[PDB]
Structures are given as C-alpha cells and as structure tokens.
Image (cartoon, rainbow, N blue to C red; front, side, top):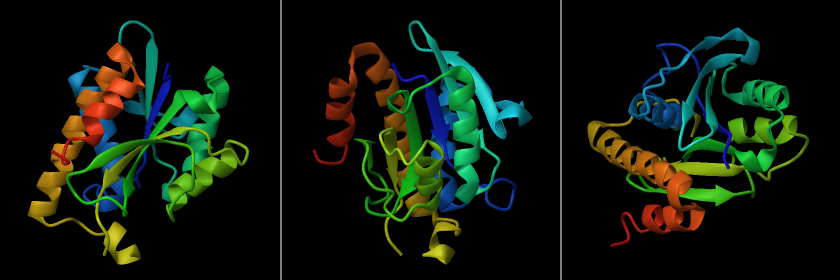
Length: 188
C-alpha cells in the first residue's frame, strides 16, 4: 500500500499559480475530496494531513522547504514513520507530457526536475519510488516559474481531476486497473 503522497511546490503567494506547483495542486484537490485539509507541521518542514482509503492510514505532504530542498521534508517524514521508498508517491510537473495528460511511473531518472533530484539524494541515492507526472508541455526557468494561460490551466485542471479519481481506484482495485484508466484518458 502507498503510505505517503507528496505534492511538490515553492512556498508563498508569489509561486502559488506557477507551473512548478502542479504537484501541490493535485494533493490539495485530493485532500478536499477526502475531507482532510492540510495544516502546518514544522517538524516535517511542510503542510500535512492524514486520510483513509479503505482502510489504512494514508499521509499527505506539501513541503515549504523551497523546491530544490524538497528531500529534507520527504526524508524527515519517511524516516519518522518508517516508510519505505516503494510506499511513497511523488506528484510533480512534467515537461515531456502536454497539458491535459498525466501518467504513473515507478523509478527512473529525474528528467531535469531539481525537486526530484533532491529526493533521490536524501533517500540515499535511491530513485525507486512512485511518481505522478502532470503534463505542462515544453517552452525553461522563466517557464516553470511562470503562470499558464487560461487554456493551458483548464487542461491541467482536467488531468488533475482524472488523476485523483484514478488514485482512489488504485486503492480499491490495484495499480494495473488504475494505470489502464489514466493512461487512456486522452488516447481515445
């Protein structure tokens, strides 16, 4: 079972609407659907909560470390609760998929994403955790710290809603079934 779901971001009103916060947008939507609002917990250097998906603890995290220091929060929380890397799901913005599309992945490279790079480092040079890749398209620093136009934002919002519904499906019926639904979303 997945025990910890992380949404990557930078802190403050300044960055709230920028592309590099797409992972946090997904964790915030999930927390609302499951009636478990996030609150500040300085022990783990971020906002946190706890939900249930029939019928075990799932913990939620959005770091306030700044993006390139994300591993500090993920490392501290996983070590405290004795959670293994294959029990972690990390949601992040993905340049190599278009707005409107999202995918699940286990392991692999960081794809240039310096939040992922810091988590791989702080888990012990270990990339073997799960990811939700939320498509934002290609442009880069100005791009990932920029705000999408309205047309692109609507498509990202569509993909995040489908990904939340497919995360609930993963807990009910398995990763294979959840993957079949999510990956065929725009391939129809």
